[PDB]
Amino acid sequence: MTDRYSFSLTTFSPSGKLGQIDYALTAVKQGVTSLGIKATNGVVIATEKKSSSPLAMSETLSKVSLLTPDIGAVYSGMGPDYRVLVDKSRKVAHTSYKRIYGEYPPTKLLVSEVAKIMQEATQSGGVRPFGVSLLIAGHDEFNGFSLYQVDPSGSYFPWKATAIGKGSVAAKTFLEKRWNDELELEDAIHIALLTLKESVEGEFNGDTIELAIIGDENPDLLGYTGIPTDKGPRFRKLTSQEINDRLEAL
Amino acid sequence: TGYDLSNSVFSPDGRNFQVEYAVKAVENGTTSIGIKCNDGVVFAVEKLITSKLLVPQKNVKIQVVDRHIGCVYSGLIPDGRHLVNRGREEAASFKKLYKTPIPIPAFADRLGQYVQAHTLYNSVRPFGVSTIFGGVDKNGAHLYMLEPSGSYWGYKGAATGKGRQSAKAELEKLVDHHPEGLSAREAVKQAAKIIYLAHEDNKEKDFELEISWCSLSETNGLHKFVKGDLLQEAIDFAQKEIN
Amino acid sequence: MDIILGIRVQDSVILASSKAVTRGISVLKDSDDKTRQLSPHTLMSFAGEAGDTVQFAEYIQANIQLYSIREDYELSPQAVSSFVRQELAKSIRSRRPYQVNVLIGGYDKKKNKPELYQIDYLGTKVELPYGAHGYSGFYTFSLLDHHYRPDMTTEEGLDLLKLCVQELEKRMPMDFKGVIVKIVDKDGIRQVDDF
Amino acid sequence: NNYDGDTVTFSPTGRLFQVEYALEAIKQGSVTVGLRSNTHAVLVALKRNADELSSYQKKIIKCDEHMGLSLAGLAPDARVLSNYLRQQCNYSSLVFNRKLAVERAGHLLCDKAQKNTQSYGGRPYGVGLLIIGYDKSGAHLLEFQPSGNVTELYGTAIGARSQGAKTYLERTLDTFIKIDGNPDELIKAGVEAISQSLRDESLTVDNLSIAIVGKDTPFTIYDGEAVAKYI
Amino acid sequence: GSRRYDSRTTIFSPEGRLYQVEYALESISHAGTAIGIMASDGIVLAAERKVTSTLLEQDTSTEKLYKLNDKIAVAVAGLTADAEILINTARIHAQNYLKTYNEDIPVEILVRRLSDIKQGYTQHGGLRPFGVSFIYAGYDDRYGYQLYTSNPSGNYTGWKAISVGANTSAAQTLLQMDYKDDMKVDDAIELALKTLSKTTDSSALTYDRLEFATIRKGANDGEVYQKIFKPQEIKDILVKTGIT
Amino acid sequence: GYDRALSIFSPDGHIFQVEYALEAVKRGTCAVGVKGKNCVVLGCERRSTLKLQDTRITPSKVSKIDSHVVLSFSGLNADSRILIEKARVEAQSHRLTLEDPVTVEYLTRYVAGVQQRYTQSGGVRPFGVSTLIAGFDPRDDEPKLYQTEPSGIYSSWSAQTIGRNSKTVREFLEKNYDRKEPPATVEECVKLTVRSLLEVVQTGAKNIEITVVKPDSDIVALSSEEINQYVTQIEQEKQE
Amino acid sequence: TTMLAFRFQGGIIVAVDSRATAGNWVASQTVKKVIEINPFLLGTMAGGAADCQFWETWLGSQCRLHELREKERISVAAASKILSNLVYQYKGAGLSMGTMICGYTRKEGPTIYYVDSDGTRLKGDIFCVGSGQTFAYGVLDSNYKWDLSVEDALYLGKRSILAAAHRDAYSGGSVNLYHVTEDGWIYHGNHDVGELFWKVKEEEGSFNNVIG
Amino acid sequence: DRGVSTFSPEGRLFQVEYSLEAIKLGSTAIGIATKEGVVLGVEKRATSPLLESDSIEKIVEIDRHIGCAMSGLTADARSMIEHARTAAVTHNLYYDEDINVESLTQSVCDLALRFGELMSRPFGVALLIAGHDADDGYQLFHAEPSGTFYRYNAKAIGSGSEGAQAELLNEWHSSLTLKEAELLVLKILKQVMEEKLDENNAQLSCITKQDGFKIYDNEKTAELIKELKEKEAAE
C-alpha cells in the first residue's frame, strides 16, 4: 500500500491552463445557485434546498453552515466536498486562532485559512481540487460586516453582493440593479428572495429555501447569562416560518 | 478501455477486471474441496504428479492454522501460503488478547478483510487463490470458501480449481441425499471419491490424493492429516467408485 | 578558562584574556590565546568549560565567515552579538548546554563607533563600556568605575587595563600567567605583543 | 503484452508475465543437476566462462554445515537468497540450538520470493536454486523457482538443456536412490546425468563443480583437480 | 501502479527547457500587468486588477500588492492563491532574520530565499511549480532602493524599471523609452500610470481597476514609509496625472 | 516521498535527462576562463536583451566560494545558486575540520560530486549548469582552473569556455593560447580573455564582465571603463 | 601512568611508562601506551585503555582514507582534530582519554596536540600526562632546550619517566622511547625501570637517598 | 513508461543491458595479470588540447595492494571508489589485515543491483580491479553494473575492447614478465586508440607485492613507448 501518488495531479497545460481547476469550476457551474448580499447592518446568504427525493428529510441536510458564532458559509458545487471543508474550517478557526488569541478569527482571516486548504488540494500530491465555490459571510469588531467568495483555486474576493453556481450570470445582473450602499438587512433579505426565485423551478417556500443572516447579536441564543461582554452569536439561520412571512411581502 | 490494466479501477460496468483475472489463475489450478460433516470438516486436494522424480507424500499442500483450522487452496500456491501466514498471525493475536482460540467465522473475516484490502489499491495485486478453510469452535463445525475479491460465505460443501463443476455436482448430490448429515469417516471417503471424479479434467497426468480433517469425536476438534490405513481405505473406496 | 576583560574607549575596543590553561593539578600551557576573529573588525574572547569554549568559538567563527562570503558584507558588531546570543539562548535548554561565556569587541564601520558586548552562557547580553566574566569583575570593576572616561585614548585604556591586571595579580589566588591583549579599531584587529 | 510492464499486473488469462520472464532467465543459465540417495545428496553444476582468459563462474554456495545450493540464472540474486538462507540457518542454530530443516528452508525461500511478485516497485528474483541438505529426516533435494514454487524431489535439473538430465534421472530413479553409503557412485550418477545436457563442450577440470552432503559428511564443494577423478 | 499517472513536473525537454516552468510563464502572461519603477527618492508599484465588477468591494480587496514587512512590498502576477502561500513564507523569513540578527532583513536576502523555494519545486518533489511572478520593491541601508523580479524558475534579477504579467514586451519598451536615472518618485508615478494606460487591454484605465503603492523616504526624516493607495487616492492621482 | 527515476538509460546507452541538461547549458550566456603565469581570469557574457537592469543589485555571474576561489557558470541561474550555496558551506566546513582552506581541485571535486548525485537519485533532475572553478591553493602560486558539467565529470583546463557559442571561442583559444608561454601578466591574460569574448559578444559595452583572481586571496572585478579600454585597444590594433 | 612528548630541533621525543593498575593491583608492567597510528603519527594513551586504543586505531583508518582521497599526507592539525571532534560528540557519555598526537610534516614541522575526552585540543611544545606527570615535568622543565641533540633529548625523556616511575606508585615497569622525524617515527627500545634505575643512579650520581 | 527493474522477454534487465551500451562508448582500459604483477593501462581521451590531461584520473588507488581502472560514465565510478576504499580500510580496522581482492570486488559488486523506485539507475561504468593478496596472489577482476564479476588473466573494456580482447587472446601466456606486460598493454592501446599514443594521452600503472600500487610517471611511460617502437621496428 502506502500513498504512492506523491506527485501533482493538477499541472499546467501548454496554454498555461490548470485543467483540474477549470474542471472543478465547471462542476461548480452545474451546482445549485447560492447568493450573498451585504447590507449596512448585516449580511444575508441564501440557497435552494434541492431535495434529491421527497422521502428525504431536507432539514437534515444543511447547505448553510455556522463556522463561528459570527461567520456563516454557503456553497455551490459538490456537497460532500463542502461538508468536509466546513469541518476543516471550524477546526482551523480554533487551532490556528482561538486557542492562540482567545477569540474567534475575523472573517477575512478564516476565509484565508479555508482558501489555503483549497489551494493545497490544487498543488499537493495525489489529490484533486475541491469541486466547490464558497460564499462566506461574517462580522468582526474592527472590519464590520463582510462577504467573501472562495473558488477551487484558493482565490478569494470580497463582494458587496454576488451569486455562484447554476444561474449566477443572470443573478449577478439582477443584484447589480438592486444593490446600493444604504440597504438595511430586511431590504437585503427581500432582494435575496427576489433574486433566488428566478433560478428556482419548482416549489418556492420556507421548506425549499435555506437562508441565514449575519446581523445583530442574539443574547437569546447564547445559552447563558451573567457576562456583560458576551452578547451572543450574530449568525442566525432563518426558520421556515420566518421565510414564508417575508414571501407574503414579496 | 484500459480499465483492466490497473487494480482497484472500476470499469464502466462497476467491475474490477484485475480481480476477475485473478479468478482465471484460480480456475487454472488443481482441484481442492471441502465437506462439512456432522461434527467437523474434511478437506481434500488433487496433487498433480508432474514427474516420477517428485517424492511421494512430501510436497504437502493443506496447511494448518492454529491447531483447529485447516486451509486448502487452488491457484498460485505461493499466494495461498502468504494468506495462511497472515491467517496464522491473525489467529495468534486473537488468542493472545482474548485467550480463546479464534472462532471460525471470526477467522473467516480476518482473511476476508485482508484479501479485500488487496483490491483497494493499484500498488498491490489481488490474490491468485480461492481458499477453502474451516474447523471446529465452541459453536460447532464451520466450512468457508474465500475468493480473490475477498468474498466469502459459509458452505455445506465447497470446491474450486479446474474440476470445480464436476466436484460441485457431486457435493450437491450429497447434500440432497443426506439432509440429516454426513459422518466424519463418511466425509473422508466421499472426499476421496470426489477428487478422483474431479480428476477427469486433469486426466493427462496422474495425481496424489491428500486429505485432512477436524472432527469433535474423531480428532478432538484438532486439525489432523489422514494417513496410513485410513487414507488407503479412502483411496480404495474412491477407486471402486470410478470403476 | 579564567580571566577575560574588555574595555571600550573613544575609538577602539580592547580585550584582555589570560594565557594559562590548567588541567586540575598542572598548568599545561602558559601562552593560550582565548580569542577568535569572527570578521575583520569583530573579535570574540571566551571562557568556560574545557572543550566547549573552543568548539563554540570556532562554530561561531565559521558561521560569520559563511555569512561574509555569501553576502560579500561584514555584519555589524550588534548583528553578530545577537546571533551569538541566540545560539547560547538556544543552547541553555539543549540536552547538553554550551558552558561558554564570551565578550564581543567590534568596531562598527558604518557608525564609526567601538562596541563591547558581554554575553554569558545563558544568553544574557549587555552592551557595556567595560565588562568581564567570572570573578574578574569583582576585582577590576571598582577601578574601572573610578578611572573610566568615554573619551579615553587607546593608550589610556591600556594603562587602566594594566592597573586592573595588577590588582588581579595581587588579590587573586590563581596564577593566570598574564594576559594577551588585543585592540579592535577602524583598521581591524592587532595584538599588543608586550604587556 | 500490455500486462508485462510490472509484477503487480495479471493478464486476462491470469498470468504474471514478469514472473514468467524471470523464469526465462533460468533457462538461459548453465545446467546444474541435483540428486540424492537415502544417505547422501549431491549437486553437480556445469560452470560457464566468459571466454578463454576468464574464470568459470561459480555455481554452488554453502549455506550451513548441513545445507547448500546450486544456482542457475542471475548470480547476484542467488547471493541475496543464499545470504538469507545462511541467516535463517544461523538463527535456528543460535536461538533454538537446532539445525534448520531443509523443508522449512524451502518454505522460507518460497515466502521471500512471493513478496516480490505481489508488490509494486519490486521485481521477481531471476534465479533458480537446487537446495540439498541432510537433517533429522535424512537426505533432501529441493528445487526453487522465483515464482515462489518450491518442490521436494529425488532428482532434478535446471538451466539450459536441463531436460536431457531430467529424463535420465527419471529412468535411473530406482538405481540411484539405492546408492547408500557410497558417495563416489552417487556423484558418478550425477556426472552421468549432467552429461546428457552437454553439446559441443565436455566436462573439463575447471568446467565441473560438484558438492555433496550426507550422514557423516559436511557440505563440501569440489572444484579443480578434486573433480578430475570423476571426469 | 501509480507511475502511470505521473506527469513528471521536474524534467527537461530535449531542448533543455523545464516544461512546467515554461507553461507557468505562459499562464502569468495572461495575468494583470504589474509595473515597478525605481527612482532616487523612492519606488513606485502599479498594477492592474483583472476585469472587475461593480459589485466587487474594492476598498477591502487585495489581489496585486502585498506587504512583506515595513520596508519591503511585492506586486503579484499569476495565481493569487499560489502567491499568498509564498508571501506568508516570506513574511516569516523576514521575522526570523529580525529575531536572529536584530536588524531588518536586507531586500536581496529575502528575494533569494523565496526564489530558492521556487527553484526547489522545479528540481525535486514531483509537484507543479508556483504560477507566480513577483516584483519586489524594498529598501535597506546597504543598497538603498531596490527592485527585483522572480519567476516560477526561481531565477531573480534586479531592475531600474520592470513589468510582469500581460503585455510586458510593450510595457518594457515604453519604460525603456521614457525612464531616466535622475528621475523622481512623482515622475515615476506618472510613467507607471501612463504605461499601464497604453498597454491595458481594457477600454480605459480607471481607479477601480488599479492597485497602487509607493515606498518613499518621504517619511519624516531618516526613515522609510510604505503607502498602499486607497481607491479615492488612486482616483486623485489619475486626475493629477491627467489620465481621467 | 517522490522517488521517480527521472534519469535513466535509453536503449543506445544514453541518459537523456543529463544530455538535455547540457542543452540548458548551451542556451546559457557564454563564460570563459583563462589562466596566465600568475593569475586566472574569468570572463562572462551579459546578454543586452535586458536593459533597464539595475547592475548594482542584479546577481553577478562570478561568485566567490571562499576568499581564494571563485565560481562562474553557464545554464540555469536558479540551479547555480544551489551549487554555489553548497560549495560555500563545504568550504567553511573544510576550514573548520581540516584547519586549512579547500584546494581548488577539492572544491571542484565536491561540486562535481553533487552534480553526479543528482543524475542517479530518485525524484530529482540533473542541474542544468556547467561551472568554471578558478583560484589558487593555500600558500601556492600555481594558477588553477577546472570545469564541471551536469553529468558530474570534471577536469583541469589551461583555458576553457562554456555556454552559447562556446564552440567559436574555444576555436579562438585553441589557436591563440600557447602552453609553453601562457599570458605572462594580468594585462595579457585579461586582453586574451576579452578578445575571446569579442568573437561572440556583440557590443563591447556592458556585455563583458571580467574578474581577475591572483594568489593569496587577491580577487577583483574590473569595471566598465577598465574593460572598455581593453575593448578600445583591441579593435585599434585590428584596423590593420 | 606517565607519558611525555616534547618538540625539539630534531623533531619529537615520545616517552612513556608501561604500568597498568586496577586499584593497588598491578595488572601489567608490559603495556604499550604509545600507539603507532601510522608510520608518521604517534599517539599516547592515558585514561581509558580501550578508549585510547580503539579511537586512535580508528584515527589511523581516517588518516589513511584522507591520504587516499587527497593524495597527500594528513596534517597533524587535521588528524588531531578528527579525534577531538569525535570524542566531543561523545562528551558526557563517559569516555576517558588523555593523549598527545605527535607528528612531523613539511608544512607544520614537528607538531604535538594534546587531545582530551572533554573536548580539549591544545597545540604545544611540551606535554606530560598521567598520575606521574608532575615528576616528569620537573626534570623536563629544568633540562629542556630547543637545541638538544637527538641523543640527549632521548635520554631526557627516558630520565623524566624514570623520575616519575620512582616516585609515582602507579607508574613503572619499563620505558618505551620513540623519536619522530619527518620521514616517520623511530623506535628506541624498551628499558626495564628496575635495571635502568640502578644504571642511572651509578652513572649519574642521582638518587643518593636510595641505597644501592 | 515502464519499471526501472523490469525484465525483458529474454530474461535480461533492460537498464543493466542499456548501461552496458554506455560502457561500450567509454575510453579503453586494459589489464594484464602476471606472476610478477598486474598491469593496468587506460586511454585518457581528452576532448580538447586545452584540457590538461594529467587531471584525467581513470586509474585509481583503492588500497596499497589494490588498484582500479574505469571505462564508461566515469563520474559514476566516484561513489564506487569511495565505497571500495571504505570497505578496504574498514576491513583492516576490524581484522588487522589486508582484505582479499575478491572480497573487495564482491563488496563493490553488491552496490550494482541496488537500484529501483536506493539509487535511481545502474552504474554506467565498468571497473578493472587489480591487486595482490597472500592467498590467491596477483589477481585481475572485471566488475560490471550487472553485479557480476569475472576473474581474468587479461581483460580489455571500453570502445576498443573486442579488438583488444582478441589481441590479448593471442599474446597472453602464463610466463609473462612485468616488463612484457607493460609493453603489451601499450601495444594494444596504441592499436585501438583513435589518436596516436603518447605519454600524455595514455597512462600505465601496476601492482606488485613489494611496492604496492603505483601510477607510472609520464617520463617512465615515455621510455616504455620508445622501447615499444624500437622492438616493433626490430622485425
Image (cartoon, rainbow, N blue to C red):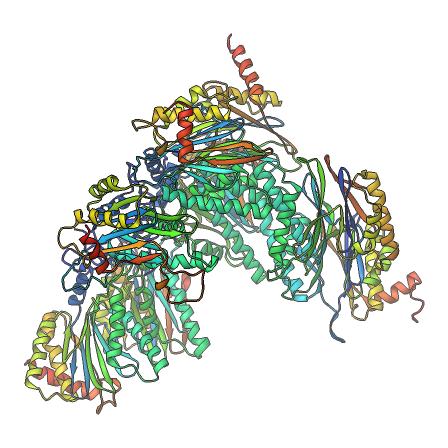
Looking at the image, residue C151 lies above or below residue A97: above
Choose top left, top right, bottom left or bottom right for residue E152: top left
Q: Please state if E171 lies on the left or on the right of G12 as rendered.
A: left
- Number of callouts: 0
Residue B3 sits in which quadrant? bottom left
Q: Position of residue G83 (x, y in %)?
A: 64, 56
- Reply above or below: D160 against D67: above
Image location (x, y in percent) of residue F86: 52, 43
Residue farthest toward the front in the current orientation of the protein: A249
The residue depicted at 53 percent of the width and 25 percent of the height is: F209
Q: Nearer the viewer, residue E1 or B211?
A: E1
Percent x, y of residue H197: 48, 32
The location of residue G139, given as percent across then percent down, is 86, 59
Q: Would residue E161 be visible to someone looking at this image? A: yes
Q: Is residue E4 visible?
A: no
Is D217 above or below relative to C108?
A: below
- D199 left or right, relative to G188: left
In front: D173, or H232? Answer: D173
